[PDB]
Image 1 (tube, rainbow, N blue to C red):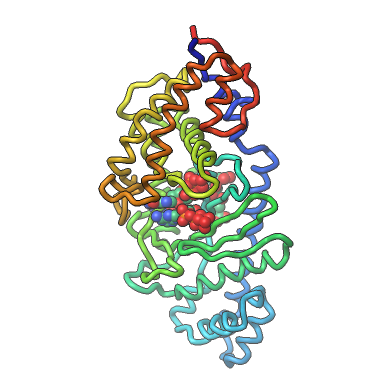
Image 2: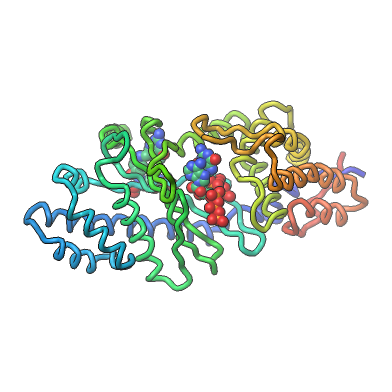
Length: 387
Ligand SMILES: CN1c2c([nH]c(N)nc2=O)NC[C@@H]1CNc1ccc(C(=O)N[C@@H](CCC(=O)N[C@@H](CCC(=O)O)C(=O)O)C(=O)O)cc1
Ligand SMILES: Nc1nc2c(ncn2[C@@H]2O[C@H](COP(=O)(O)OP(=O)(O)OP(=O)(O)O)[C@@H](O)[C@H]2O)c(=O)[nH]1
Ligand SMILES: Nc1ncnc2c1ncn2[C@@H]1O[C@H](COP(=O)(O)OP(=O)(O)OP(=O)(O)O)[C@@H](O)[C@H]1O
Ligand SMILES: [Mg+2]
């Protein structure tokens, strides 16, 4: 007997899609969390700009600057951090100070929350994440921007830390590409990567936008590296977003669904680790662009995807952004223990899907396919006998 799994995957209630898509409680909870961080980040920058504006008018001692800082939200930084902030503001150039007084922090969400691939967590320790980037409109720079890299990082840290001090169960964590607020009890964390963009082009596009009811020069979108050798690196997140969105248009609405399923499979096989979300997306896109498939039957499509995935990761997965210094996934001749473990799981997937298809009953078919996605869908009646 052959079983069809289309309803198993796509049913918005009892199906896998029904288990992966965020509830209104979780979705609005993430939006509220993002709103709080955006408000605080802007308020913190205004407080810092207020101190700098006082400096501009009447010359203040470094002593007075440090006491002003201690009263603001910057106080939630360490004593050494508070002092450097007061030092940077005090030792700031006259021309550099004018640039800062006009600094306007902007925000734009990237990642799965933006292109709607965000799944509900499965195993303990797994969390939902919002990738809300902060943009700093400044003049184009080559090496070091007008407004210091150190100052921008500290002010963002102060904003995040000030929110942690106001919430039990919240914790701050610094990664290489962003600052992070972790909410363990809610299985949630928000990442805040900082970018530098051309102020002139930003104002231009903003003026045209408001009058019409717009991506800037990609080479001038600089990501701030916290612990890296380089303070800045040209990493435009818009490249990945446009790539995936264009792929969804080119391939169809079933692309986001199958991408969710592979990520759910990833969450089921590893409590932590496994292939990156972007690597799964890129590989899946390559398959649906090269191999014929039927969107009306995502059960067959997933089988087709699982069949070709191992060869995709073996070849190595190229990044949608050619600017990337590394591929999303290494080729076979560069595989270590980590990649071999991933290859082992990938080769196992198609066997699991086939086994579930040849099960003796709906009940048996459910638990077999649940080997790939874990126990989420409990309704075996979603599985129908193949015509
Ligand atoms: C990203 N971007 C980008 C560009 N170009 C290139 N090459 N790379 C880039 O990364 N161009 C545009 C943008 C960079 N420039 C801008 C970034 C942010 C803003 C701005 O006014 N943001 C608003 C919020 C936008 C939002 O919530 N938006 C919502 C969308 C609507 C909603 O969710 O309700 C959201 O963030 O989810 C704000 O700061 O309050 C204005 C311009
Ligand atoms: N160019 C480039 N961008 C990346 C890479 N990895 C992550 N990013 C960016 O970082 C953002 C967040 O990526 P992830 O959180 O790992 O992927 P995701 O789609 O959010 O997956 P989940 O977080 O598991 O839902 C993405 O929107 C990408 O733009 C990479 O290797 N190259
Ligand atoms: N090439 C890149 N360019 C810009 N940002 C990136 C890039 N790769 C990852 N990021 C950022 O890092 C986050 C992805 O996290 P990563 O894959 O580094 O593991 P992690 O979440 O740091 O692991 P852990 O949760 O154990 O700290 C994304 O939210 C993204 O904003
Ligand atoms: Mg993410």
